[PDB]
Image: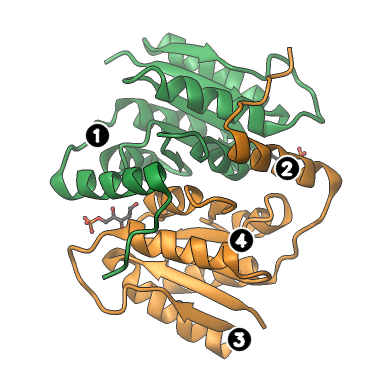
Chain colours: A orange, B green
């Protein structure tokens, strides 16, 4: 069982509440970063930055950010130092996010999937192991070093 | 109408990148190849994605496309570049919303996830859909930009 930080604007809110209940039922500890109620006009970035910041700060935890499409949400998460947020739109991409990218977070577009599809995405995300494979780690290290220095790494050739 | 487009890809997105480059030329746009310049099965996506994102941000009004197996590590990398907003485009709808809602200057595309026809449809939506300039979207982009400026997490409501 794992702590999972969730953040969502109004467009992801209802799906977020469903995911929280699903995660409880499957033995996880969901932590709601907000929104705590439906507010049709609310703004995703704060919730996504909160979820990403909290996830990165909490070893072994994962996070999930939801909105209409999930794309603004993952962009916002990805601005957090050390955060790696994939956009998960299928079981395959949720799984690869963990296996290849060691993503601590995924974005999900609430308007893009049925609830069943979304929960299947969440299941793949929370159950797929990070591979620890050499080449994937190398690539993550390159990105982390760019985050640290903003020195663009040279392109081969 | 015609857009300048910076492209970057690792080996997993290489063939698709070359097809997109030709497609963009054929449809009246100006593709600029940031690499990879040949197929290297072992090469590492971050450098190419950071290059494309960095050049896109430095050339306002340009767009960028980053490609790899899933596009997710690729967009994560792009999103580390100051001022870059890179959506994951997995459909015509999400490519369009990336422009409309997120004003994303870049998209990631997974070369292992789509047929070429499907990929080119995604590209067409991305390079043709206008940024909406709607108040609420500009507000959210500005909130994210301020967080990127200071790395001070904005309070949730
Ligand atoms: O990437 C952003 C996500 O799709 C948002 O939930 C969406 O933009 C919200 O739009 P609206 O409900 O304010 O029209
Ligand atoms: O996000 C990363 C992208 O999916 C890469 O193209 C992928 O990791 C390459 O996988 P492999 O060809 O090294 O197995």
Residue A36, above or below A50: below
The chain under label 4 reads A
**Identity of the residue drawn at 62% across and 71% down:** A61
Q: Position of residue B17 (x, y in %)?
A: 59, 23
Disc 3 target residue: A26
Q: Which residue is denoted by mark 1 in the rendering?
A: B131
- Mark 4 or 2 closer to N-term? 4
C-alpha distance separating marks 3 and 2: 32 Å
Chain under numbered label 1 = B
Q: Residue at x 59, y 40 (%)?
A: A147
- Mark pair 3, 4: CA separation: 19 Å
Q: Nearer the viewer, residue B26 or B133?
A: B133
**Could you tell me which residue is drawn at 35 percent across and 41 percent down?**
B98
> Is the shortest distance between ligand 1 and the CB of mark 1 under 8 Å?
no
Q: Chain of mark 2?
A: A
User: Which SS class for mark 3?
Assistant: loop
Please give the residue where the numbered disc 2 appears in the rendered image: A141
**Mark 1 closeness class: few <14, some 14–19, many ≥20 residues within 10 Å:** some
Tell me: residue A27, above or below residue B137. below
Q: Residue at x 20, y 71 (%)?
A: A39
In three-dimensional space, the C-alpha distance between marks 2 and 1, rounded to whole angstroms, equals 34 Å
Labels 4 and 2 in the same subunit? yes
Q: Is residue B97 left or right of residue A136?
A: left
Q: Which residue is mark 4?
A: A104
Q: Position of residue A67 (x, y in %)?
A: 36, 61
On screen, residue A44 above or below B114: below
Asked which quadrant contains residue A135, the reply is top right
- SS for tag 1? loop
Whether disc 2's CB lies below 8 Å from ligand 2 is answered no
How far across and how far down the image is residue A98, in percent? 68, 58
Residues at marks 4 and 1, CA–CA distance in whole angstroms: 30 Å
């Amino acid at each position: 069982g794992m702590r999972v930080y969730l953040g969502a604007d109004h467009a992801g809110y209802e799906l977020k509440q469903r995911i929280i209940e699903h995660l409880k039922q499957t033995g996880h500890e969901p932590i709601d970063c907000g929104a705590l109620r439906y507010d049709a006009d609310d703004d995703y970035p704060a919730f996504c930055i909160a979820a990403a910041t909290r996830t990165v700060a909490d070893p072994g935890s994962l996070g999930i950010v939801l909105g209409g499409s999930g794309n603004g949400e993952q962009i916002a998460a990805n601005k957090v130092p050390g955060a790696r947020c994939a956009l998960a739109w299928s079981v395959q991409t949720a799984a690869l996010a963990r296996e290849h990218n060691n993503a601590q977070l995924i974005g999900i577009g609430g308007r893009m999937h049925t609830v069943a599809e979304a929960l299947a995405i969440v299941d793949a995300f929370v159950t797929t192991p990070w591979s620890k494979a050499q080449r994937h780690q190398r690539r993550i290290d390159i990105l982390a070093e760019y985050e640290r220095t903003h020195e663009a790494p040279p392109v081969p050739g």
